[PDB]
Image (tube, coloured by chain):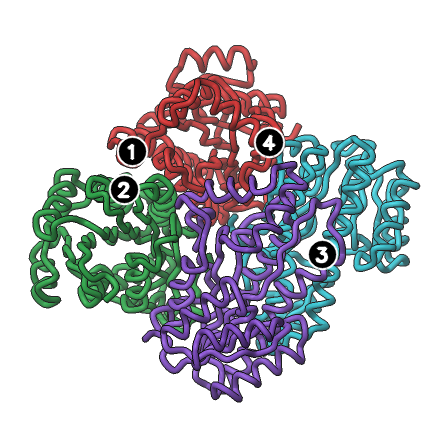
Chain colours: A purple, B green, C red, D cyan
Amino acid sequence: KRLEGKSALITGSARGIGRAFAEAYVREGATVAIADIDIERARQAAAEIGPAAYAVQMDVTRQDSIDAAIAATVEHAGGLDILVNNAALFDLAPIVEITRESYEKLFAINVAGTLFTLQAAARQMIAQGRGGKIINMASQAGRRGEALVAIYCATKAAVISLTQSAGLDLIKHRINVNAIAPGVVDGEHWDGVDALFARYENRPRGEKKRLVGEAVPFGRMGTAEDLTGMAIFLASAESDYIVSQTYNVDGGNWMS
Amino acid sequence: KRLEGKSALITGSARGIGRAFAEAYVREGATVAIADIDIERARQAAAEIGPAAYAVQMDVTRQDSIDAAIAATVEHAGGLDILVNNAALFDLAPIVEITRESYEKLFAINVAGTLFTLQAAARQMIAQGRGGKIINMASQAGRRGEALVAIYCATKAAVISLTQSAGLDLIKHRINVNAIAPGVVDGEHWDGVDALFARYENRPRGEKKRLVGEAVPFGRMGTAEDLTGMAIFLASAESDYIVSQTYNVDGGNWMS
Amino acid sequence: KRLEGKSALITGSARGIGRAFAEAYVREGATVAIADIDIERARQAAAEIGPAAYAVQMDVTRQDSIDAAIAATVEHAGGLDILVNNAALFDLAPIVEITRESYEKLFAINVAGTLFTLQAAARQMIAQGRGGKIINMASQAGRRGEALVAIYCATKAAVISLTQSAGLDLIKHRINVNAIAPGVVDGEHWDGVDALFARYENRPRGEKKRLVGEAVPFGRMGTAEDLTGMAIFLASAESDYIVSQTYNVDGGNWMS
Amino acid sequence: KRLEGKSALITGSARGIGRAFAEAYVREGATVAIADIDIERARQAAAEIGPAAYAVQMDVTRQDSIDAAIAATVEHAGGLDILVNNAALFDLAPIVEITRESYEKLFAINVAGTLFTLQAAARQMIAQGRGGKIINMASQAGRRGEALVAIYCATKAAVISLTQSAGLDLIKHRINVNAIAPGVVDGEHWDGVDALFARYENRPRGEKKRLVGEAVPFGRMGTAEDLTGMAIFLASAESDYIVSQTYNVDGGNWMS
């Protein structure tokens, strides 16, 4: 259907939102590179999704790994039509406990990883002369700061800015750069996230995750399936005029 | 396809963007009330589009007209699933030449018309108990002021706000309220728009329209067909988690 | 000191924030017109503030009242250098209970009153050829919608838009148009505001006012004296380069 | 004398906007640490500004240099009441020519430098128990992306994000964290900025600088003296209620 014969690469797609996007894209006729640092699980996820999906080992913190992931897409799929920068790390600390290690690690994956993957995808798309779709994964966190989330908020704000900058620079090549800003999405990560808020806000385990879910205007915590519609749309021809946008898909958590 | 069995009303839909949306909605399986003050052209538009499109006489500045248009939808289509608030009026004047007539006429159509049609559709949607989709038509003008466009900018700014408020208030009824913000769209209206800039900015006729089209990062003035994908998406199930958003579909003219 | 010899008019300044601005302006050596619909509370306010304050009857919904106030200002003070558009009305109701009466009342005062008072001060300031300072009173309400507060949020959204448009059009006359967005500010008005939230959110009286004050990141409900710094600053020569901005003074309630 | 007896440190303040801030703070009765990587231009700046200014060698990319600078400030002035994060580096390049060297250098100074200097100042201000004032230097660049300026735009976007997060976390210690966003500001740096744009947009030298100055709605390129008003205000008691805001002082270049 909507992505018929398109070749996609989704960073960090072995599980969670990225794997949901990869399954949605295969259903819509795309060939999909399940790019992940977890090459074992990616190989698993590709085998389960079907012949249209194939595993690619990728660490977005390393230039050589980014360049070999793109080349791998050219090898298997004939080229690259759609990049989703999905790989991300979360962290939480009050200002006076923020570590250089936290700053370096989250900026390396969330910003540099996105920026240099986007740059390598753009180079391939410019060389093909057929245009392209790039979708960055932002967050409600990139829309506004939080006392305890300065580092991840800042990374996601840099993503929104990069989305804007790259979108204006690459549209002359018929490459659309846009971003999705999820709200709060349910899954295994919330054990960590809830723990981190629990400690600093002094809460019973699971309280944070309960309150956050109940405060989503829509009435529940997000699923990956909430986001797959937008992911297909922004990779499809029905989004050709859409440039340098961040679209919140977040049950009303943040209004942009 | 994506709006199979749905009942929609698009205000001001005899011409331009609204008619484009009605044709797209019809092609996606919707029944569409082509609502316009211009009942003659609505009748012509519905006849060309097909059996699924039907003409409704509507002046969004009058409560009795709004209420009769919604009732007419219940009569013909069995109910209302989708409202597109498309009817709007443009004007331009420096601050010192703004007239109470310009203020009253633009606020009546662009704000009161959208608000009270949204209210009437919401009331019908709540009574049905099947949830709903409301799509307001904002504009780049609602994202930021312009020296010469204080009234229209203010009206579209009010629309973005109303979209946010109504979205939070109505999502407990499973009614999604969102908005589309076009940039500059080609069509008959630019005679008026260029003429108004031409005067105040002291330009040959057709210059403003030309410069504005060439300044769109995408590389051209918009069409109604740039917007139809978003119109369908925000009326469809693939947008169910999206609440109180304004989405720019504008070739990069404004980055939100 | 910083407004020595300057002629100001503050709309709705017999009480609350407007009156705190008039006292601060007089302290800084401005002559101030205490414009109010209540001419008796104005005369009181002017008697108490001192000889540099003087009472002007003004209905900002009436063009004749607007022009008569500016003329009175010119007659008494030799002209007008600072306008503060402080006259506003609050109201609250969910979408399905919004009345045309609420819509019309809040837009007439909050939007038309600001726009046509701004327009009348601009004409006067242009004729004088000495430039000017115009300060619009926005709100956190103008920064984002709320389920219960569609009409008042929409009016404050239009004020921010109008502040942008007028700022751009009027700067060539050396008139600085900017706005202040308070968050929650204490005063007699909060009895009314809490009562509305109490009624429609079904709360004990004073619970909303208490919760609202405690959620301010700064840690308290704001005072008018929190805002007087910015009100002086934006009418002083230290803000000459500041154009078409809304500045939140809100203890962190909204981040812009 | 609005900053009477206050201890300030301004990063990168030997020249340009930082130096203007140091002179203005001294005029207002502050003691000011002229922190710069160039200790010679720091000493010369401090000698010229007068006895209340003193030179501090500081590399904001190095934690040991950061901590040694805060120490020197406590040593000389008795403590730290005001931090201005002014040290920044500009660079320009389209997406496909962005180097890892440009990314790393601009993020180290513009983001890490601001964050870790803010953290070192915060710890000192908390230990003191007297509250304090932190002012980050943002930019128009941080408010929206540009095709050629992805890296610098992204760093300034992260500064606005960090300003929001820090402000919310530190207001409980009576530390106000806010930011100033200049538009285009004159100085010896604009030879370098114009040259980069001349290079990558293929323009005669000085055309960019001229065009950007003429596009400021106010009608000229900004001066550092345009910004000192706000730099004093945000460090003074008239801004005590102002938390997590970015204030554009840009002649209307960007409207927030």
Q: CA distance from mark 2 to mark 1?
A: 9 Å
Q: Is residue D173 above or below residue B88?
A: above
Relative depth, front residue between C194 and B170:
B170
Q: Is residue C133 above or below residue C23?
A: below
Q: Are marks 2 and 1 in contact (CB under 8 Å)?
A: yes
| Amino acid, disc 1 | Tyr
Q: Chain of mark 3?
A: A
Read off the residue under disc 3: A102
Q: Is residue A86 left or right of residue B188?
A: right
Q: CA distance from mark 3 to mark 1?
A: 50 Å
Q: Chain of mark 2?
A: B
Q: Nearer the viewer, mark 3 or mark 1?
A: 3
**Residue B104 pos. (x, y %):** 26, 40
Is any atom of residue B96 visible in this view?
A: no
Read off the residue under disc 1: C103
Residue drawn at (62%, 22%), measured in percent from left and top? C27
**Residue D225 pos. (x, y %):** 69, 47
The verdict on a common chain for dots 2 and 1 is no
Q: Chain of mark 4?
A: C
Relative depth, front residue between C207 and B225:
C207
What kind of element bears circle 2? helix
Relative depth, front residue between B37 and C93:
C93
**Mark identifier at residue B115:** 2
Q: Nearer the viewer, mark 3 or mark 2?
A: 3
CA neighbours of label 4 inside 10 A, class few (<14), some (14 to 19), many (20+): some
Q: CA distance from mark 4 to mark 1?
A: 32 Å
